[PDB]
Image 1: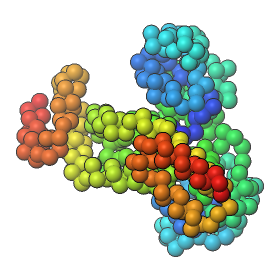
Image 2: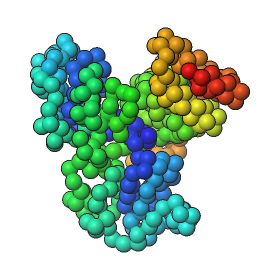
Image 3: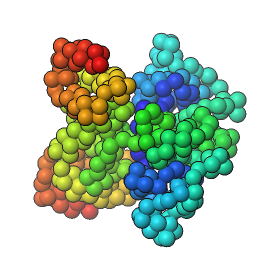
Length: 196
Length: 199
């Protein structure tokens, strides 16, 4: 429908539920800057393992209005009809909520600042799974520190008091395999722009 | 940032600005069921046509405090830095700061489609040029064969959903049809359609 990038870095995420969907959702956005709370009577072995590693907070309760305060993003993973109704009746108008609801989560992966998301508008989640695998293979962890390098370069060049002509030159230069796969190449480029 | 589909159906959307960037942004959510209001002293020929077609509302003036009060999603797509700054609203407020350099909490990824297949690519603004490169590289690998194929897959989904056969049979069938040969053989496709008719 309408695909966007959403900043969750440092933001509050509540997951309502603790079964298999809940576990999937959390796996999905763990890398994202967190503040994850899970509210359910019972949770899964996986949520338990994450709770135990300091990755998540759990509240083994029936969700109440006290759980729905100032949460940036709410995920209602559960199917439990009454819980879904309750949450829907107790959130504000502009509440981001994945359930109605106003947030769908597509298959995706990231390599630091790089992200690729795939959908078929529910025609083939199984194709989407295959394409995700193929793309994860083709875009590996080298893109994590490369896109971090790119990001530093963009900020640094932006700040330069150097002509538009030169800025564009510096921004074009750093887009090839040799910048991704050579630390000398990167480090020397950084030495160059530091001098300006 | 994290990738999500935002459902704007029956939500208020404010587009601040009315140039080329505002027009491009609106195109993206024009068929989404939102109530779109566009605020700029002047607006493009295409925004005008959309207004005249009754798909959005136009406010022909510069933005003021009032315009930002009860708006679910704000897109800033102007060129006057004071408008940008002025908009730059509460926290928890969805906003796309399209006109850079700094971000809102909403970014719009590069996207291409092959029929129903959709790919979204972002580098969190690290490099618009890399994003373009990757979109071209993905365009190369996923060509127009995927446009026809997701149409096949869609029809299969429809026909399999209303089969009076088990859930586990449905899954097996929907799994079966995911490989290169289903995509690239029309015989394979057609014989499978015929097969799921018997059930």
